[PDB]
Length: 395
Ligand code: HEM
Ligand SMILES: CN[C@@H](Cc1ccccc1)C(=O)N[C@H](CO)Cc1c[nH]c2ccccc12
Image (cartoon, rainbow, N blue to C red):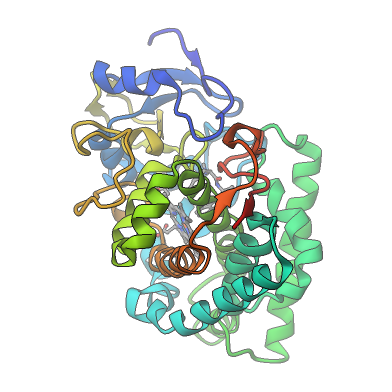
């Protein structure tokens, strides 16, 4: 194999993609790389190629649990349904699929709408400037994931310390990663226990009933599944909505487009998912289980592949002018939610939260503008997802 290049190519800066990704797409080759932790891997960068590795059966995600997973984090993270192949993946997803369907999530829109109203009610009285990350983006995603799952949002003062340890690359040392992670796995266990004595009318309550009277999941599958849903809803969604708000407030000709044309919103939400590079670098690695050829490379059974999803979302062979934001694109086959088997489970819930919050922010602050130069806005350094630390605005 070729000499392995360091990966990452550098810290992810704001929302800029490193130039090597585009050259790799043009080269039509995988790149053998050397990551901060785990085995070496092949970096995958073309929309066509990232689709193959995300979902082809010959590329396994279970096979990486019996390995020191190529990865960017110090510790291997438990990814629940995201770390298993079928039939374990089937068995487990079916337990949460109906709650996260488009029809299932449509019922949450009246209350998501009303929260966005109560949150925007408060910027009005508070007055500029407002930190949109603190006063809006985090209360919205944080209160909508906790109310669906059953986690007390009023418990955020203890478990949002622990959520950062799952997303750290260089922000925390590995000993502080290991300890916050077990703090979280013991807070989840607290909640599972409080519901065998006191059944709840929430997603966690229904998962505990599902392990107890059906045995449809082991107890660590139970606690992992619930650990991962609050991971994704409380922080991954806030990152994307905080970064989409950066893209509109710094390219303010697109905020003016969508504000004058709110019917664009479902298209505007999709393109903001294609165009924002939410994943700092790569998604979860897969290991070949037999020999697959792609990207001018015979990947042998047992080798890793790292899918660089943000790069696939700029593939000129799929997206006309992929580096220009076009909030009005009609067909958007982006991979910002994954592809095939592991396609993002809260897809519909991210969309609804994003349609509502963008429509009302733009509708209700028609001259909303950043209260700093775009480059004076601070960004998450060392983290697995990209996000602005604060987002001061005025109107
Ligand atoms: C803007 C916010 C989000 C983004 C960008 C996002 C992105 C993704 C992506 C790209 C994948 C596929 C990963 C891969 O194959 O490597 C994925 C899988 C998944 N996502 Fe998220 N997600 C978001 C919010 C959420 C929310 C709110 C939930 C649940 C409450 C969620 C739960 C999941 C689950 C459970 C999986 C694994 C599904 C399976 O393995 O069948 N995500 N997500
Ligand atoms: C290489 N995973 C990185 C990058 C990433 C990948 C996908 C989405 C967002 C960000 C990460 O931050 N992963 C975070 C932090 O561990 C956890 C996570 C994100 N999506 C998940 C789905 C199921 C279980 C866990 C997760």
